[PDB]
Figure 1 (cartoon, each protein chain N blue to C red):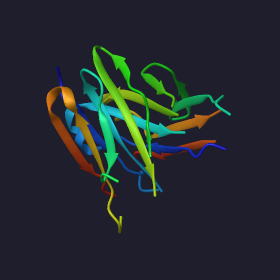
Figure 2 (cartoon, each protein chain N blue to C red):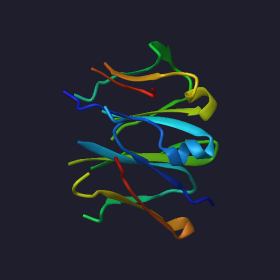
Figure 3 (cartoon, rainbow over the protein chains, first blue to last red):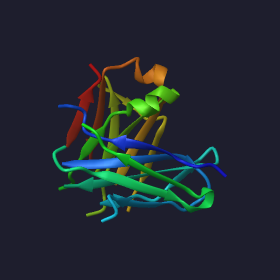
Figure 4 (cartoon, rainbow over the protein chains, first blue to last red):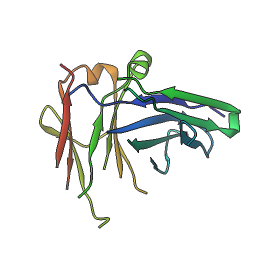
Length: 81
Length: 80
């Protein structure tokens, strides 16, 4: 078993946001945004799952909430400019 | 008309030594990745519900300046 690393997806200083969930095992993983959007199916490589989820909407705040039941792990990564 | 969005690696990931570039996109669609203009095929993993993800080592990411997500429109970002 392995908890996932969650990475924020913010635009490259140059609105859609997202989160990247890398290296977790096993499935599944639940993804919500500030608990109330596109969560793509996972891909399996090297025995680890990776997934991503976007959201269309800095003044107001957005935070993706990713949960991994298997390892009783949670992660809530705010997206910063 | 898909609304494409491209994203650079986060500092958090880079700190761990990896570099993933994410791109959010009739079903038929084709995504092409470019690094400094030339096509890159290895290290790409796709998902459809579309999302394309180019993973590289930090060293490799640091070797180039431009990353481009090209659909079937072109969206990109320069590290510098």
